[PDB]
Image 1 (cartoon, rainbow over the protein chains, first blue to last red):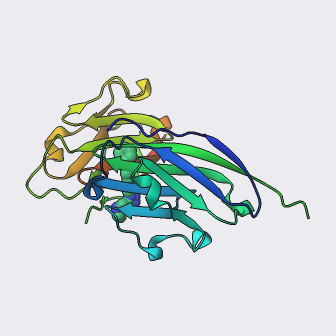
Image 2: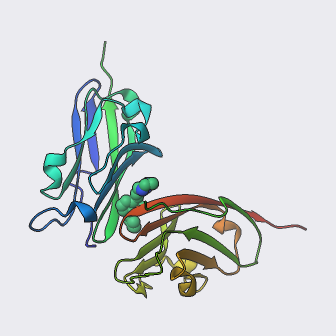
Image 3: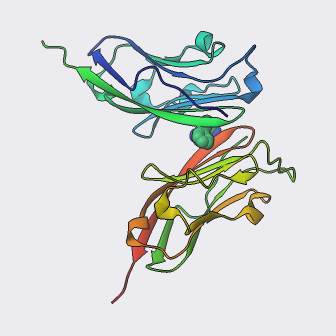
Length: 118
Length: 117
Ligand SMILES: CCNCc1nnnn1/C=C/c1cccc(-c2ccccc2)c1C
């Protein structure tokens, strides 16, 4: 169980930059993939669905296609790290990470996107 | 595998009646309390937190204090049944059941409240 903990509740980013938003969870030794579920969401649009190690491209929302990815490397450290490359204005909003790894919690994260200033 | 399934996505209810909204989940005739978590929420108000056998009373928001309860009887049958008694207009809105039982899924249910005159 415990609690999902978030380093930063707000990320302010540049248009066309990259960002990695993070949700930490209690890990403790190795990662038992059978126990792990990570869902990232915003505005009820599926960004990531990780289910015991399974991800399907097809479930992802098109706006996030080929840009958002979950850094599997950080998962073993108890860090659900969503990385979105080439941040779009439309990506501004509230993100929900939902994690289960022997008990479950969710946190909300806000994103503000600065204009490109053409 | 794990998918939360809802009989009714909308409930239209009477003011001052009771309602019971339900979220079904896969149980294999097993029903391991230690594994099960049920969170009911609406408009970011915690209604129920069933955690590992017990209802957590403390975290329930005081608007749903003596009114919302989880039907424990149904849980064994893979049915997270939130019952709220004496429905107020304020109880109209979108409910989110989050269930974790060896894997995890959520669904939204909308509630519309009638009062005839
Ligand atoms: C359909 C395939 N299954 C995966 C899936 N699909 N939609 N959502 N989802 C997973 C959701 C999830 C994942 C982890 C924890 C919690 C959760 C549980 C209780 C409290 C807080 C958070 C939830 C609700």
